[PDB]
Image (cartoon, rainbow, N blue to C red):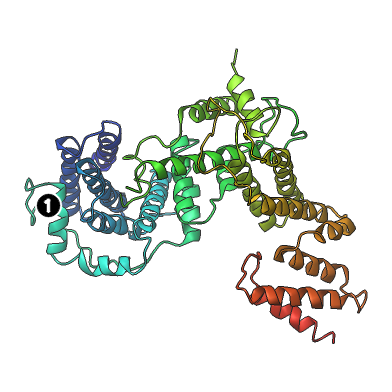
Amino acid sequence: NTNMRMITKELLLAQCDVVFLTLSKKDVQKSKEALERFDQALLSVKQSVSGTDASDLSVTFYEMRGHYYMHAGTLLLKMAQSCEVQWKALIEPAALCYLLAYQVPKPKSKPDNGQGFLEELAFDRQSKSGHLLLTLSHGKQNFISEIIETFANQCGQSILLKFLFEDNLSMQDSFMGSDDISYVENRVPDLSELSQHDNGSLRIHNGDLQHLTWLGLQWHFLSTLPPLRKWLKQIFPRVPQETSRLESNIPESICLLDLEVFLLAVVQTSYLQLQDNNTTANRPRCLPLPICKQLFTDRQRSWWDAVYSLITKAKLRSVIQHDLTTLRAQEKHGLQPAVLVNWARGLHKTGYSLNSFYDQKEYMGRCVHYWKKLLPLLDLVKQKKSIPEPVDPLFKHFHNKDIKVSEVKDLEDEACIAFATLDLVDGKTEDAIIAFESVKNVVAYWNLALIYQRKAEEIENDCLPAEEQEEFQECLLKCKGFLKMICDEYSAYPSIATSLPVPV
């Protein structure tokens, strides 16, 4: 009875998704037929059994309403791609469809009928809809205009119904007309809620390389690094966070930082590859998960599958061992500088942000290791071949990776600052100063002033003029609008200027 009305909606949803992606219906009869059956079932269940608060039909109906609008958006984008490419007329219909799904509220009875399914489906729908609503509406003031236009009493839903089912369904009857939408308002997803929705969506995509690289790419498009450690702690719970030795290429000593580094590299290589794939001559940069093609190459897939088979278990591990040698910058690697430098900067930031001492050291140890392994190779930049890689080992790109002769100096300075900071977070506070008195950028000045303050809370007076002149240096350097410091001088400069005047 009502239970079959419950389950058929779920099965028709799975049918719609499968017919959409793997069956690769080319936006022709194949997929639109499933969508039409879905819409018919929706109107049928809504009009007759208007479930109240008590029956679960109402909450399942709400979740499938959100999912129906999401799939409407995906079908619009597929039509646009198949015909020519994502048009200028099929992103706003699609943007409105993505919005409504996120806006209908996550289902929670909180008292049998495993609400877990609806909970994780809400996780997934919100994650997807939000990531595709930010990447479509990258420019602001776009949501407000779409909300006040593409929707209206009937015209808005008419121009959204005709596209999906071309004149095979009446407007008033058996359609989306009976559903009212005017109840939705402007509310772009939050960058904190989005990360938790992704951390939840990882509950139905355990270790899917495609899904992970898609999420990584979507975060990368928003110009903020993704939270790789939460996801990697969810996927793999137990894996050690570091290793005893970085000099040994042994397969059964996988550290979580290795997988973090591998995912960083895959995300950047796939991003550059698509960037060169005639996207410069397509409005959705990343093309939602089911419609888009493979983002990683084949060797990455083989290695990740071997790693997953090792972790979550006559095993041939030559791929593990070979790419581990590649990963730890060991005996002989084909990767050029662009990859090592990205690795080092990422580990640097991720470690420095955190507070736990046994975590900052770990991030600074791996960071200094990568910079010191870059040290000799970047020296081979004297009108010389970097590394002959006629074959592509794992990550080989050109016209980007090649570090020109000029930029060497800055990487040297960053490596020295990494050395100083590593030793400063170990307790050798004197040679920390020693090393910080060679590089002459603003990071050095700020770190020196900070160590002067901490060591000398209530020690001496004349050590304060050290802080005085170093923050005067940083003042002149602020005069040039230099925002390179981790905390902007709006906060450091005022506090230090105050402390200097108060001590005076």
Q: Quadrant of residue 374?
A: top right
Of the residues shown, which amino acid type is indicated by label 1?
A: Lys
State the residue at coordinates (34%, 43%): 278
Residue 248 quadrant = top right
Residue at the top extreme, as displayed: 314
Q: Residues within 10 Å of mark 1 (few under 14, many from 20)?
A: some
Residue 80 in the figure: left or right of residue 346: left
Residue 78 spot, x, y in % from top left: 25, 43
Q: Is residue 495 above or below residue 423?
A: below
Total marks shown come to: 1
Report the side of 297 relative to 325 (left or right). Answer: left
Q: Is residue 492 in view from this perspective?
A: no
Q: Nearer the viewer, residue 332 or 159?
A: 332
Name the outermost residue toward the front: 383
Of residue 427 and residue 474, the one placed in the foreground of this image is 474
Question: In the displayed structure, does residue 277 sit left or right of residue 213?
Answer: left
Q: Residue at x 36, y 42 (%)?
A: 289
Disc 1 secondary structure class: helix
- What quarter of the picture does the N terminus occupy? top left
Residue 391: x, y in percent?
53, 25
**Vertical arrangement, residue 51 with respect to residue 262, above or below:** below
Tag 1 residue = 162
x%, y% of residue 46?
19, 53
Where does the C terminus fall, quadrant-wise? Answer: bottom right
Q: Is residue 465 above or below residue 401?
A: below
Q: Nearer the viewer, residue 304 or 424?
A: 424
x, y percent for residue 285: 37, 49
Residue 159 seen in the figure: yes
Along the horizontal axis of the image, is 426 left or right of 2?
Answer: right
